[PDB]
Image (cartoon, rainbow over all chains, first blue to last red; front, side):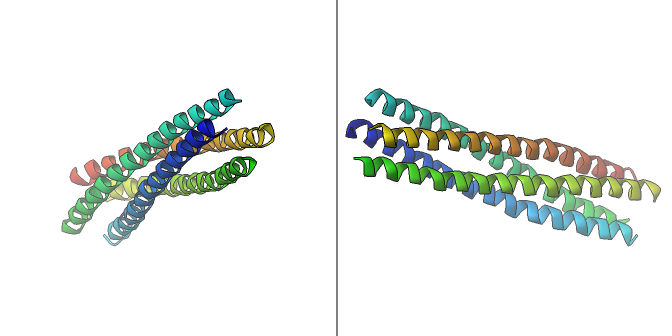
Length: 50
Length: 50
Length: 50
Length: 50
């Protein structure tokens, strides 16, 4: 049983650690993208105002 | 069987690799969009001077 | 034990939920950025008319 | 053994199906983002040219 179930458990833990790093990276993308949207929409208002 | 457990563990390693590729995609998109924010800030400056 | 295997299976269900949340984040970002393309095309039209 | 190993296998298959849908969704984001970058950089050239 436990040879393979312990290595499988370890594999799942590693997968979960990778998932957390993916979550964190894509969160940074979302945060940057918010800024991009704001600055593009400001640029739109600026061009409209002239 | 132990063979079945081993197959599952190996399965999870490929999953980890695919998570890593997604993490790299979020990384690249974040850097691209952060640079684009800078371009848009330069665009705002250009428009204001005109 | 069977308990150990069950714990791993339940573990994978939470993983699926976290993958779904990432999928939703990519979905939202794609829609936002596709709309932003449209805004930028309108910006190009504004600038060309000026 | 196989009660729990079969449900764990099924759980992993479901997780993999979700991973594929995540990959596909984030690919669409990347494709849209390419267009956004191009159109912002065109807008930059247009503003520079006037």
